[PDB]
Length: 191
Length: 191
Ligand code: DMA
Image 1 (tube, rainbow over the protein chains, first blue to last red):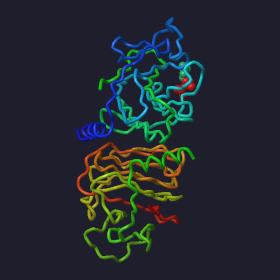
Image 2: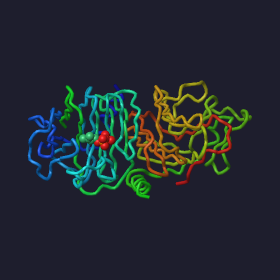
Image 3: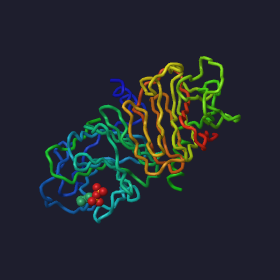
Image 4: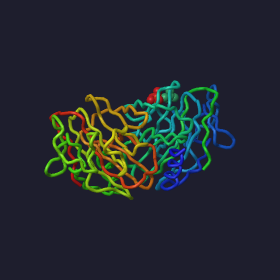
């Protein structure tokens, strides 16, 4: 209905539609990236993969194949009924090898779901969210120039979370994190 | 200071500062508008005022003196330690005499506070807000073209609420509502 149409018209009016694909070279070894680079699952156990510098070795993260150094961009992710997932953006310069907390101070702007029902923003400390309708599809919205990262229910247009406006250092990558083994993959919607 | 600075630079990149004054001709007869038209209080009982067509006769509402038919606008409101208030925008065509529920379907976009601690967006159904620090000062952000109404803690830049993007009909007015008789006024910050 009207709320979906207005969500469509807003994203079209102001945000460059990103066509995002997963970069398997960056993916933590426990992650499985689909051949078409749209879908993300977790393996039972870490695969034997090279620890090249670009690969996340601690966090169960993967990046997109393109970064943003300017402009407004959006993309949508089919989270469906998956009980655990976090998505957003992170800086090129994040710690990929050693333990760090995924927080804006450490260069990550992400939100998501734990244990089926606990929505959080990964602020420091974590922000417990109240979500009246669990999203099946999440829109990720970036405005580089104003330091804005926001998240919507892409089916009904309802707002989920907006980080405080910040200042970004260097390129921002789409980032995806899953900690659990379960049937429903994360799937990127094509532009 | 960084969150405050980014909030300031965001308002400057995108939103025209509105210099909002209260129109006493619109004010429910239980409301008092200050001589400088920036402050709002509540009377013990309705005062004797003309029932001109613009006046809210049921709802404890008052409008700004200027409407918006286009563009990006913000204003900030000092709610201070008030236990109760609602602010936002409404259409020119809202029902002013009969009761109507203050919902987007009826042409009202407001959030506020009840009972000192219950923050709500007056969506339908109402959205329970979780607010980590009670705001003293609230920024109201309108984008007419994309049908966007959003609200921020104007002192730390944290986001409070964004309504689903919608389609506005006709001019929008700043609206302000207080239901309680309590020591702290509602006061508009000058541009
Ligand atoms: C691989 C792994 C156990 C990461 C989760 O990080 P965390 O326990 O600090 O939690 P979160 O980032 O979800 O707050």
